[PDB]
Length: 581
Ligand SMILES: NC(=O)c1ccc[n+]([C@@H]2O[C@H](COP(=O)([O-])OP(=O)(O)OC[C@H]3O[C@@H](n4cnc5c(N)ncnc54)[C@H](O)[C@@H]3O)[C@@H](O)[C@H]2O)c1
Ligand SMILES: [Mg+2]
Ligand SMILES: [Zn+2]
Image 1 (cartoon, protein in one colour):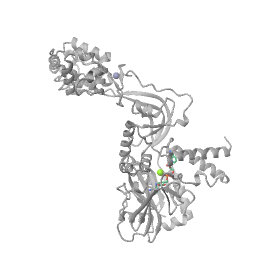
Image 2 (spheres, protein in one colour):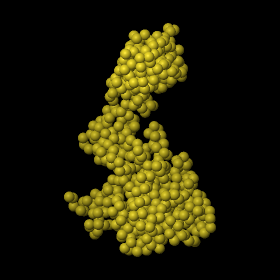
Image 3 (cartoon, rainbow, N blue to C red):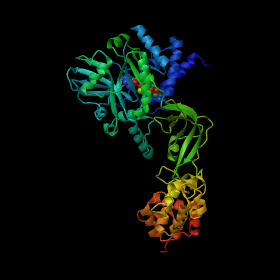
């Protein structure tokens, strides 16, 4: 289409743009898979037109320049990247190229974190650096000493006088999710994924910040080596590092054929959801150091290793709509409907938006291109909007003011992330739990109205509100499973007796959000009657001891919703009774 010269400048500009956001800012806008796609396109163009490769092309360079706000460390041996493949056929082609230019493979989990180079002198940790641009990195020595998995001293015989240990610092998934949940609720930085949370946690001027983040580390390789020797195979070196106290993954594996490599790759992909940390693939390395040294390096990567990538855990797609799911207790979760896309190999077409505050934090509009993440058998999540690709036609996301299931008021209370349907007494989405609550022991306490009886009444649409329970005839109950004429009359009798209650237990039975047994008793004692309570403003409700803004808001919004007032009127009409004050 466009001239090859225009294609080249566009690709180089785009790749550097995202390299800056990823390597320098730990804040990428596009998925790793999209960057990898663009890099493949540039590689294909340069392979067809090798005369157009420049020494500063992204295919010839590593990482990004180190932040000058950090002290800087010149690696004593260059740090590089890895060239990659995405399918078995391409790995086999790499295997053949290697065989024809010289084999045992040392095969390792490819950890999705950031690279670090740790210098030990006489077995003592003396410095540690990020990769930077492969020549100069950022001094993160103080930060690395907060990482328990990285030893400060090596213990053993034959420790070389000077040794750079290289490995990946990374942040397990549970630690990542905690950091992001906290950040969403406090206004801090929300990270795209564990890689970026690990990088941002590590690359702190103040190491006390790093120390509070659950970073860990695995070794994977060697930089400078002086004043001593190491084993003559890569796995041998890793096992020596392990003996000296450095952390080595228990999945490092030898393979004596290309087909063994494929078997390991596929088992690791199968085991991926169980590991507790992100891996973007497996790294496959010529095991013999002599063979590694013969093959050497190109500008960006070794010629003796390949990153065999998995289908990526983040992908981009378009938001076609936003649906608002109503949960069993009235929570309204915004869920994006998406153009279908495979994430980590699994076809998905929705993703959670968490809540209304998160929609606003994202800046999401219908029609946006978004990054979504799926790591495990869970609903995917929207990560961010790809704002640089926002179409000219997008639509505002209007969070519902009324429940999409029952039409009752939706409530959002300041400081609370979750919006809720207020119509707990009528909402179909809440009906099973609301009726079970209503007849429970500390509420109306109806003998024989068990969960399986309630389930049938709801599923057959025989009951829609708690008032309908008192309208049940013995004949209608008899028609249910688990019910006979005797138990049907038993529960009709039990419902008639249950009309005798207290103001506190009736209030508790209504199922207002956050109103526990003690709060119900306090509201009943303060206001004395239902008429006084149902009239109270939020400020009036806040007068009550142990009732704050959240409970006051829920109570006021509950009684302001017409469907609740209608059910309460019906309950009184059916004869529910409590003592006057
Ligand atoms: N989303 C974006 O905008 C964006 C931008 C630039 C780069 N990236 C991502 O960065 C990567 C490309 O750059 P890169 O140089 O960081 O490459 P990489 O992470 O794909 O491969 C090289 C790295 O693998 C790491 N590694 C992990 N486990 C290893 C093991 N067992 N043995 C050896 N090395 C191991 C090393 O730190 C090494 O630097 C791709 O994942 C790319 O998608 C993303
Ligand atoms: Mg990486
Ligand atoms: Zn509702």
